[PDB]
Amino acid sequence: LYFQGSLRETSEGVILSVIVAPNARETKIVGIDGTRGRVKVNVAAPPVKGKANKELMKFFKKLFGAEVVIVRGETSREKDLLIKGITKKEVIEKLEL
Ligand code: NA
Picture 1 (cartoon, rainbow, N blue to C red):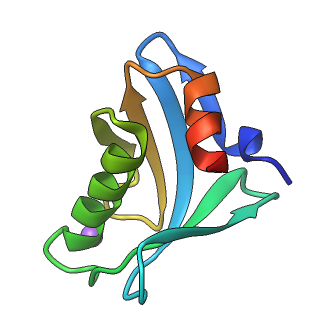
Picture 2: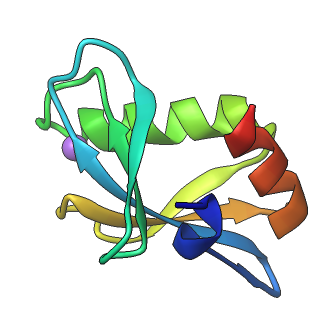
Picture 3: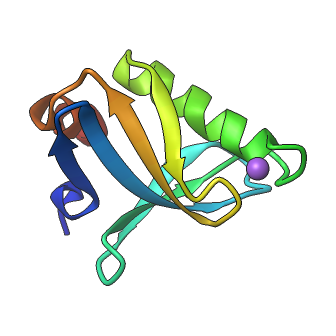
């Protein structure tokens, strides 16, 4: 399994497709879902008042050094994140760290 199955590069940056589990001990990448083409992300926040979405975005903004917005799935576990102004090569390097 490679992270490439969860990413695609658009004119605006990289869409990173994730599947979250809230209430986690630590916000971190725990795996890849090879059927859904998504990175499994544990989020150390409750899924109330948008707090899991906020923590998810904060985690990836820090990892990538780039603005991260949710473009689909604000109220779903399966969320698509636009990482603005970054290339797929840069995203792969950071996910592989
Ligand atoms: Na949330």
